[PDB]
Amino acid sequence: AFFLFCSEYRPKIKGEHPGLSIGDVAKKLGEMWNNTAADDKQPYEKKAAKLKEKY
DNA sequence: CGGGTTTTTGTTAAGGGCTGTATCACTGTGTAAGACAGGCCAGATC
Image 1: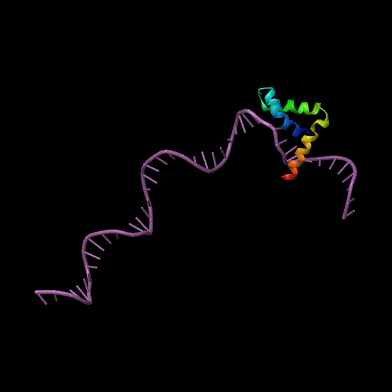
Image 2: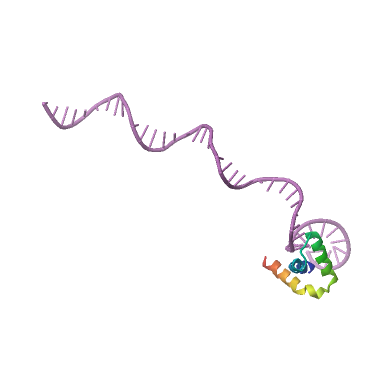
């Protein structure tokens, strides 16, 4: 569920910060998705499951 | 025959670095195509 949350927060991260490296940005997004509650990634996980079922 | 427990792969998030082909202006160069100068007539004329 954290993968779709990271994918959805990547544009927010690029808007809040200019971005220096994709690796550090991805690490920070993963750390944030792990520190936040699991309910925050529920619609993201639902959209990921929908995209997996459609493809 | 069938779940439990355990042992291995995929997934997309991304701007990068790295490596493998595909292409692009360049000409040159081999090749059938189809035209053309004769060759060989059979018919018209004095």
